[PDB]
Image: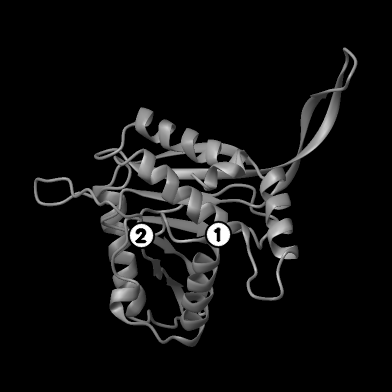
Amino acid sequence: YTDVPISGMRKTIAARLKESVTENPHFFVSTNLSVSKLLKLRQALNSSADGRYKLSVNDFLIKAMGIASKRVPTVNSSWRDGVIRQFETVDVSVAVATPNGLITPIVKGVEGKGLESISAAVKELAKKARDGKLKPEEYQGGSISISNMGMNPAVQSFTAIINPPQAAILAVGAPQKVAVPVENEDGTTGVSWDEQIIVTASFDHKVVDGAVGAEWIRELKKVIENPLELLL
């Protein structure tokens, strides 16, 4: 009936996603991260401030992605002319939802940067993405991506398409209350309510195998569920 035409900008993104799904054989690895200690650490770090900063879960996730990509360097790679290009630093592309679609500004040098610097760079790039004032060197590049959907409480889990020429992409669902067993100080078991987040990582099988993706997911889960390991 109504036949509004394609903008032309959508055609390049459609061809790019076509390239991604036709040259990257994707496989997904799902996990559930417990963030009950991460939320307490974020609450303490936000309460011990004078309005200098404001921390979110995405800052801890980007720092944990940097730590996990430094520990497993096979995921921090690409696919080039007969050659695998392996980087040292973790450059994390963060997806920002604008009314003109999707853009991925890059936070450069994630490992050894600082949570306040990460929060400042994410806020700068997000407000500049909403104003539409970016340079091509700010959204062209990166070694790993992350898609965030925590503001929507309906999305329990979702998958994402890998932006070429990267090798992996993360997808973070809304937190939910999951029943987790607990021992009391006597012999019986109990019911405790834990805040869990379903995290799905999509890997390219030409670069990352299933054991390498499982090791990356295990290190990410370790750094998330033990928040004091973000110091190291």
- Along the viewing direction, whichever of 180 and 222 lies nearer the viewer: 222
Q: Secondary structure at mark 1?
A: helix
**Mark 1 or 2, nearer chain start:** 1
Amino acid type, mark 1:
Asp
220 relative to 5 in the view: left or right: right
**Residue position for label 2:** 91
Q: Relative to residue 107, is residue 203 depicted above or below?
A: above
Amino acid type, mark 2:
Asp
Quarter where residue 53 is shown: bottom right
Q: Secondary structure at mark 2?
A: loop
202 relative to 64 in the view: left or right: left
Q: Residue at x 28, y 47 (%)?
A: 24
**Residue position for label 1:** 59
Q: Relative to residue 101, is residue 62 depicted above or below?
A: above
Q: Residues within 10 Å of mark 2 (few under 14, many from 20)?
A: many
- Along the viewing direction, whichever of 9 and 140 lies nearer the viewer: 140
Can you tell which mark lies on residue 50? none
Residue 6, x across and y down, in percent: 37, 79
Q: Residues within 10 Å of mark 1 (few under 14, many from 20)?
A: some
Residue 224, x across and y down, in percent: 58, 43
182 relative to 74 in the view: left or right: right
Q: CA distance from mark 1 to mark 2?
A: 14 Å
Q: Residue at x 40, y 54 (%)?
A: 161
Q: Relative to residue 190, is residue 24 depicted above or below?
A: below
Residue 150, x across and y down, in percent: 63, 58
Q: Residue at x 56, y 59 (%)?
A: 58
Residue found farthest to the left: 82
Q: Residue at x 44, y 86 (%)?
A: 132
**Colour treatment of the image:** one colour
